[PDB]
Amino acid sequence: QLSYDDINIDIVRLNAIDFKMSWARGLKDILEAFEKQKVPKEVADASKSNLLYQQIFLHDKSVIEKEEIYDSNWLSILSFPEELRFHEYNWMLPKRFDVR
Amino acid sequence: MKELIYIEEPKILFAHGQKCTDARDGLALFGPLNNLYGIKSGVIGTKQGLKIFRDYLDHIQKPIYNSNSITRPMFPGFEAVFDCKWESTGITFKEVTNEDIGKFLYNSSTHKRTYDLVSLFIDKIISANKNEDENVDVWFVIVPDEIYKYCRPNSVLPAETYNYDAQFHDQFKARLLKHTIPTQIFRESTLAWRDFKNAFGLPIRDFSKIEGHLAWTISTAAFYKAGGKPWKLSDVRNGVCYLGLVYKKVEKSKNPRNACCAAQMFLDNGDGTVFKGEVGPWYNPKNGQYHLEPKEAKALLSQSLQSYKEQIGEYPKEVFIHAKTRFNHQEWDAFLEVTPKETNLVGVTISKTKPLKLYKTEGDYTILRGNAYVVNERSAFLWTVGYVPKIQTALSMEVPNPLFIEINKGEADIKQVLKDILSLTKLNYNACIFADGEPVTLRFADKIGEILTASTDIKTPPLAFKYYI
DNA sequence: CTAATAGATTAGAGCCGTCA
RNA sequence: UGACGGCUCUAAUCUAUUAGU
Ligand SMILES: [Mg+2]
C-alpha cells in the first residue's frame, strides 16, 4: 500500500528483497543473497536443513518455451473409391445367404 | 501437424493468504486454513486394534521422510503441520470381543453376516453417541483383514435382510446417516503393515519408501473428517455454479430402477468455496436408460437453484452441468422450462473411451500435463494426467490417455471449460496428491450415489461429505 | 416380441503397480 | 475400506435392415 516515495530515505536506495507476491520466492532470494554474501551458516541439523533448503528453489519450477513434436497412433486414410453401390438382387440371392 | 495449447496450473490457497501449487508443500509452509484446537478420537475394535491405532498415532507425531524428497515431500509431524493436538490421550476405547466377530462370520450367507457385523458395530457406536457425556469427533473403526476380504458380493467361504448390500463399507456408512457420526474405516494391514506378511518374510503392502505419503493422506483425512478446512481454490469466479451428475444402478431390486445423484460447488461471496452434495436419489424405472424424466429433471434443477438462492440470494449467472452421459431433448427441455432468464445452462460430457495417445519422439518421459488438443468449437482433448515439471515425474506409469470434452448443449468457450475442469481437480480432500485425473464434481457424486444405494430406509439424507467419504 | 447382422454408447467388478 | 493410475473380463440399452406378427 506504500509507494516508492513513502519509503524511508535511509533505506530506499538499498537493494530490497520482495515478499509482496509470496513468502517463498522471497525466501529463495534471501537464501541466494545470504549464500552469495557469505553469511556464516552453521548447519547443526543434517539431512533436515538441506531438505528444507531444497524445498524452496524447487516449489517455483515451471515450464520453458521450447518447440516439441509428438507422434500418435492415428493413421489418416488417404484415398476412397468414387462410388458406393447398391446392387439389386431381387430374390436373386438366397434369403439367408449370410452376405458377410 | 496439428497444434497443441498448454494451460497453466490453477494454484490453491492456504493460511496467511498464501497461494502455492502443491498441497503437500502448502501444508508444510503455511498450514491449514481454519483453526481447530485438537481432535478427540473414538476407537471401536479389538485390543489389537487399539494397540495398532495407538502405535500409529504415536509414530506420526515425529517427522517422517521418504526415499525421494522431490517426488514425495517429507512429512514434518502432525502438530508441525496441522496446528492441533491429536495424540493417544483423547481416545475412548469400546472393546469388541473377538468371540462375537468370529461367531458371526461363519453363516455361509454373505448378506446375513454383513448385516450382523454392521448391526453389531453400529449398535455400539450409537449407544456411545446418545447415552454418554463424552464428546468424540471421529469414530475410527479398526477392522480385521478377514472381515474385509469376505465382505464382497463375489465372495466364497473356504428376505427381511436381503434388501441390503453384501459390503461392510456401504452398509456401515448408509445405516449411520440418520445419526451423523463421522467415521473412518481402517484395516489392520494398513496401519501396521510390518506384521501382516506372506510366506516370504516380507510385508504384503510394502510402505518402506512411501511412509510419508501414507502419513500425509491419513492425517489429511482425519483433519477433514473433524471439521477442518485444509485449503481452498484460488481463482474460481463469482456467479458460477458447478454441478455434477452421475447414474448408479440399484442392483438388488425388482425393477432396474436406475438412480441419479449430484454435487454442487460455488463461491459464497465470503471467499469460501461452498462444496456439498445435493442429493435425493431420483429414479428412472426404465432398464438401461440413463436419462431423467422431465418431472425429476425439473425437481433436481429446482432444488439446486433454490439451494444456491437461499445460500446467496441471487440466481447464478452461469450454470455448468457436468456428466459422463449425453442428454436427450426432453431432459434438456425440462431443464430449460424451470430456468430463470438471467442464467446460462451449459452441459459438458467428460468421456474416457476415446483412444488418442501422444508419444514424445526422443526421451523416456511422457507428455506435459496442461497440453490440450482442440478439435472444434465444441470438442477437445485434455491431458489431466502427465508429466509435472515441479515433482520431476508424472501422475501415471504408462503412457496416459486424455479426457475427451464436448460442450453438448448451450453456448460457451471450450478453453474456459477445460480451464475450469482442470481447476476442479484440486479438491480431493480424501487424498493428499498433486492433482486428480478427473474433476471432483464427478467423483464425490459417485461416492454419494454408491453409499445411498445399498439402503432403502433413508429419507432426507445429509449433504456434508464428512459422513460419506 | 423374438431371432440374428452391425455401429455407437453406458455401467459393474476384479487385478496389478507405486522404489531405485 | 489410506490414495491414485493403467488394463482385462462381463452384462445391458438404443439406432438402421431382414424373418418369425
Ligand atoms: Mg476415505
Image: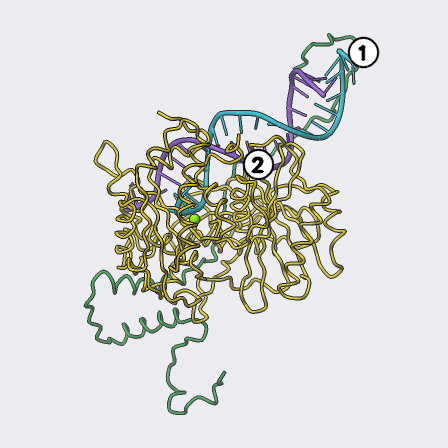
Chain colours: A green, B yellow, C purple, D cyan
User: Which mark, by number, is residue A90?
Assistant: 1
Q: Nearer the viewer, residue B300 or B204?
A: B300
- Quadrant position of residue D11: top right
The image shows residue B50 at horizontal and vertical percentages of 29, 49
Residue marked by disc 2: B250
- Quadrant position of residue C6: top right
Q: Nearer the viewer, residue B74 or B153?
A: B153
- Quadrant position of residue B100: top left
User: Label 2: few (<14), some or many (≥20) within 10 Å?
Assistant: many
In the picture provided, is B363 more to the left or to the right than B410? left
Q: Amino acid at mark 1?
A: Asn
- The chain that hosts pointer 1 is A
B41 relative to C6, above or below: below
B200 relative to B231, above or below: above
The image shows residue B371 at horizontal and vertical percentages of 52, 50
In the picture provided, is B413 more to the left or to the right than B43? right
The residue under the point 74% across, 51% down is B336
The image shows residue B34 at horizontal and vertical percentages of 44, 67
Q: Secondary structure at mark 2?
A: loop
- The chain that hosts pointer 2 is B
Q: CA distance from mark 1 to mark 2?
A: 50 Å
